[PDB]
Length: 146
Length: 143
Length: 147
Image (cartoon, rainbow over all chains, first blue to last red; front, side):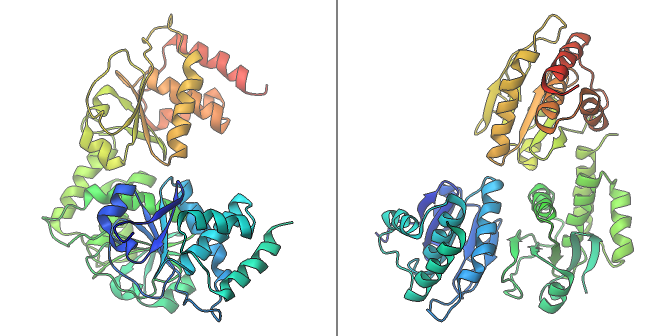
């Protein structure tokens, strides 16, 4: 519900909306140490003492999001190494932030787009990348898998 | 423009932080803002950490040294470059840099200060900060 | 010195004495998340909200400290993996805690006893394992390193 917050994807990886990124007490309770914002608007909300990375990407099929997969994945892996927790987020937490997490599951966990998608779908049912992004995920799949 | 303290560590002001072109040319990959205001300026695609501290002797800045140092070591390990900055680039950001030289390179407060002094002469931590730096020296170094 | 505290060995590994383990504000400033106590006495000091492991060993040549090396090392690697920091300590911070740190350098970084010892010596000069422990360190070197 709306009383809920970011969902856990992996121990070090959470997914969520812009609203979730603004609930500081909530992020503190989860021990979130970094924010990877994928929208186009910044919110100083809960930014202090936190590893932050902004990779603005509008939610459109015209938007190229796959070319930023590497930067985003490196960031998440950085947090992983330093043993912290990142909350990857975007405006609604439906298209962008979940597209990135899928890319992550594929690149570091060898999941297939289908497996990456259901896995995230199981924790945040409303998840749904715009047709352009899903398209880029498909090309991305072919590139990193046999 | 920002001055190079170490290959992976640059020191500057809020203004310097907003000059993207300049950052890009130096291959700046991260920013550590030690002021109380954020400037959406050149914040995209960059490891950013914001530790707000006011430039007053009443301000506790020493207890944020480790967090700041670990952050700079991270950029170090990832082979990048951090631009530590604060409003004027005189008190806050340079105090962190002194702390960094002391903790990682074993510099003594005196040597640390002179080191940064040579790169940016105007540098000068408020007397409270110099005080915390001295207390800091005694804690991370022999007698 | 005296106003001084734990010394850094590795980013996730600090060495020190029982006294250093009791200076909570100091541990908090360094971001110490765990304590590995190798003395025979526990000190409720700064124990809250911290990964703690107690491996009691007396500081004597008759004491077997080498067979606890792996337990200590796994513990340190755990903190390392979780991205935290352990302060390994013993009463004086001269024999026990530094012996463990040497063993750690040998097992995970492949340092030879000589290099491990100098490395820790440079950061805490008074370091000096009792002759029994140095002996065990030697047996230990031959067991985990080529010749």
